[PDB]
Image (cartoon, rainbow over all chains, first blue to last red; front, side):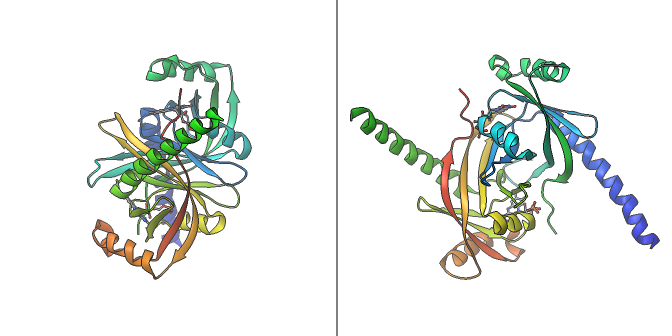
Length: 147
Length: 147
Ligand SMILES: Cc1cc2nc3c(=O)[nH]c(=O)nc-3n(C[C@H](O)[C@H](O)[C@H](O)COP(=O)(O)O)c2cc1C
Ligand SMILES: Cc1cc2nc3c(=O)[nH]c(=O)nc-3n(C[C@H](O)[C@H](O)[C@H](O)COP(=O)(O)O)c2cc1C
C-alpha cells in the first residue's frame, strides 16, 4: 500500500518536472513547434505555430496571423496538441507534447496586446494579428514514451 | 477553355512537384518526422515516426513497433497527417505535409517484408515489428501557405 503511495509522490514530482520543461520549451518559441488539430470529419491537420507564451500552470496564449485551417479546426472541435521537437538530425531527439483545448478567441485585451508585443519582435511583425488564441493545458507528456 | 486548360496544367506540375518533395523527405527518414492522429472523441495525438517509405504516388508504409495511442487512433478513425520538418540551428530549411488514410494493417506480405528490411537497418532494429501500416496518400501540402 505505502509502496503504491510513494510511487504517487514520485509521479507528482514527474508532472512538475514536465510542466517546467514544457514552460521553457514553449516560451522559447522554437521554429520547430507545431500544433495539430482536427475538423468534424476527422481530417487531422498540423501547422508550424511558434508565436507562443505559457501563462502560469494551465494556459498557453498564441498569436494567430495565418493558420486558416488550424483556426477553423479549433472553432469546430476545440482540441489540439503542441509539440516542440529538437533534434541533431543524427541520433539526438528531445522536446515535449502539450495537449490542449481552446479556451478563448480574443481580438483585444492585454492577452491580445501581449501576444501582439511578442509578434512584433519576430519575422512575422508585418502580419496582422487576427486572433489571440487562449488554450487550457490538459496534459503534458514527454516527446516519446518508449518501453 | 484556355483558362481551364492552363490551370489544369499548373495543378499537374504542382502535384508532381509536391509528390517528389514528399518522396524525398519521407524516404530519407529524418528524426524530425511525425504522424498526427485523432480518436472518435476528437482527441488529437502526435508522435515521432520515422521508419517509413513512400511507394509510387499513392502509398506510405510504416513500421509499427511502439506508437500505441497513434495505432489505437488509426484503428478508430483511420485518419492522419505526416509531417517532415527540417530546421538547421533554428533556421527553417524545408519540409512537407502528407495527409493520409489507413488502408491496411498487415503482419505479412510484400509491404511487411519491405518495411522489415528497412527497420533492420535502424537503431530500433531490436524492437519487434507488430504491424506494417499501409497508408493511402490523400493530399500533400507545403509546410506553410502564408502569403
Ligand atoms: C526518432 C524517432 C523515430 C521513431 N520512429 C518510430 C516509428 O517509425 N514507428 C513506431 O512505431 N515508433 C517510432 N518511434 C517511437 C514512438 O515515437 C514512441 O513509441 C512514442 O511514445 C509513441 O507515442 P504515442 O503513444 O503517443 O503513440 C520513434 C521515436 C523516435 C525518437
Ligand atoms: C517558423 C514558422 C512559425 C509560424 N508561426 C505561426 C504562428 O505562430 N501563428 C500563425 O497563425 N501562423 C504561423 N506560421 C504560419 C502557418 O504555419 C501557416 O499559415 C500555415 O499554412 C497554416 O496552416 P493551416 O492553413 O493548415 O492551418 C508560422 C510559419 C513558420 C514557418
